[PDB]
Image (spheres, coloured by chain):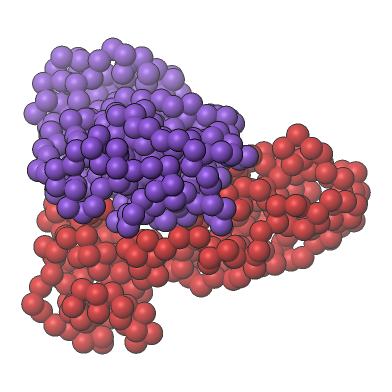
Chain colours: A purple, B red
């Protein structure tokens, strides 16, 4: 009995964080092999951000205009280029602490850890999900840009996110490590709509299974449902439609608990239609959607 | 525009975690200098745990009964001893990655990060509070024993907790790094009562300030209260009494927001008496008490290590 949101240990990523300064702007970079990766908006003034021409701004920059510091070590920049919304600064030294790593573009509803940093130094670690609307519900102050999101599988770090923007609505957006934004967003200070923030249905179901495994079973009811019937209710409550692929992913949790996936769907349907009536599940007063099936299996 | 339960970066602690096996029991140890610290119950069989005489059990153990592994490197144990409920294994190698560190005994209501480990390998990190009844609401599976809790000030790691026990009620108990349990608990597999728990009032207030700083202000009222009047309501709802020390601790958050501490107390009073009526605060449907005032300042000011 005990179930918590957990981040990956951050040590492998801490060894890759550097500070990047261009003019008056300082933010975070990621140093892997002999390349430092950071948001291209490092080259922008506050004024430039309203309507930046990144190509023209970068052409006014030279290698020596990029100050890159890894702890107390100044790195020597020997080249620069822009890949989508990320700057790649070639340095003359490979990071001796480069872990085994991959760049991955994650799917909506998948989770990852963020190492929040300021001025190239780690502040803290927390677990997030890529929302279906391609925003992330985090904590990123001024100077946090270039902080990264990651998953670890044994010794391999899969980087999936680099932080770029806070939208006027207070939500956060960023890119993969090839510099492509998740979602429709751009690296400009303008009004930008995130779409409807749908709930990640398969993750809620995974967490209900986690609740059963940990002895919190009050919400189990005597009903079943069909995918199509359930989805009519999901749609009404701004939940993601459930597919057979999702049902299949939940199969191991179904097996462990003896509760068929559509039976759990019927329990969720009743919770949606009736509310939780002031009750808690795993100590939460609302339905949690930022644990994946894999996350639940790992912890359970 | 965002406020999250945030753990400290774990890198300095990761370099100190090892696996300790004694017979059929494997759990985690903390390797600092040439000492590995772990729960003394590593020396117990399942049977011994029901009523162990640790002095007698330790006497029957030899150095060669303790297998210690740091990654794939087996360390050689050259001595063993007991300090309260923690076993200290002397090894023939000093940990080259030993950080600047202290051992501290934290107060109820204070927070710390746990590096949950299994068989000596770090698995994840999360932020916890020491409950008023000296339990932890965490996630500690079989093999997680010997995982440690810590805070970081600048470059210094302050270890404050080592995990020992899952009580039959599913809550967790452990020790400081001198092996003294927090609370009434013992390292025996027996029924053990945890006290009545209470909600950490000063931490709820700090989190309400965090909400205001992040633009969530619906629960602010133009009502007042006194400390004594507020505490009459706190008592009814199993909240900790608020003291002037607590008011003083909240002063910087009061200053930042322009909201007097007793004014925020009046807001909390109304939330307790009336409920939240289906509304959320910082995305939560209940009042969060596992952020200290210092935690709120740290996260809102972007302190680094």
Residues A241 and B196: in front is A241
Question: Height in image: A26 above or below A214?
Answer: below
User: Is residue B35 visible in the rendered structure shown here?
Assistant: yes
- Counting from the top left corner in percent of width and height, residue A15 is at 56, 45
Residues B173 and B178: in front is B178
Identify the residue at image location x=32%, y=25%.
A107
Residues B122 and A263: in front is B122
The quarter holding residue A108 reads top left
The quarter holding residue B288 reads bottom left
Please give left or right for residue A200 compared with residue B10 in the image.
left
- Counting from the top left corner in percent of width and height, residue B54 is at 80, 58
User: Is residue B172 visible in the rendered structure shown here?
Assistant: no
Identify the residue at image location x=56%, y=57%.
A72
Residues A223 and B302: in front is B302
Question: Height in image: B249 above or below B195?
Answer: below
The quarter holding residue B183 reads bottom right
Please give left or right for residue B260 compared with residue B173 in the image.
left
Question: Height in image: A179 above or below B83?
Answer: above
- Counting from the top left corner in percent of width and height, residue B253 is at 28, 74
Identify the residue at image location x=16%, y=60%.
B216
- Counting from the top left corner in percent of width and height, residue B79 is at 89, 55
Question: Height in image: A212 above or below B255?
Answer: above
């Amino acid at each position: 009995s005990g179930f918590r949101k957990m981040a990956f240990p951050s040590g492998k990523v801490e060894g890759c964080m550097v500070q990047v300064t261009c003019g008056t702007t300082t933010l975070n970079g990621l140093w892997l092999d002999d390349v430092v990766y950071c948001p291209r908006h490092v080259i922008c003034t506050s004024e430039d951000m309203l309507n930046p021409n990144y190509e023209d701004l970068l052409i006014r920059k030279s290698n020596h205009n990029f100050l890159v510091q890894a702890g107390n070590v100044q790195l020597r920049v020997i080249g620069h280029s822009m890949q989508n919304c990320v700057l790649k600064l070639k340095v003359d030294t490979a990071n001796p602490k480069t872990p085994k790593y991959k760049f991955v573009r994650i799917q909506p509803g998948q989770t990852f850890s963020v190492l929040a940093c300021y001025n190239g130094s780690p502040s803290g670690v927390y677990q997030c999900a890529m929302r279906p609307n391609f925003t992330i519900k985090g904590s990123f102050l001024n100077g946090s840009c270039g902080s990264v999101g990651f998953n670890i599988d044994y010794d391999c770090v899969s980087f999936c996110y680099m932080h770029h923007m806070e939208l006027p609505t207070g939500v956060y957006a960023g890119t993969d490590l090839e510099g492509n934004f998740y979602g429709p967003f751009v690296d400009r200070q303008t009004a930008q709509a995130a779409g409807t923030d749908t709930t990640i249905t398969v993750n809620v179901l995974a967490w209900l299974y986690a609740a059963v495994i940990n002895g919190d079973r009050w919400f189990l009811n005597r009903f079943t449902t069909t995918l199509n019937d359930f989805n009519l209710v999901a749609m009404k409550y701004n939940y993601e439609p459930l597919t057979q692929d999702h049902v299949d992913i939940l199969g191991p949790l179904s097996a462990q608990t003896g509760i068929a996936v559509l039976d759990m769907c019927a329990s969720l349907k009743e919770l949606l239609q009736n509310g939780m009536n002031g009750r808690t599940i795993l100590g939460s007063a609302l339905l949690e959607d930022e644990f994946t099936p894999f996350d639940v299996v790992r912890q359970c």
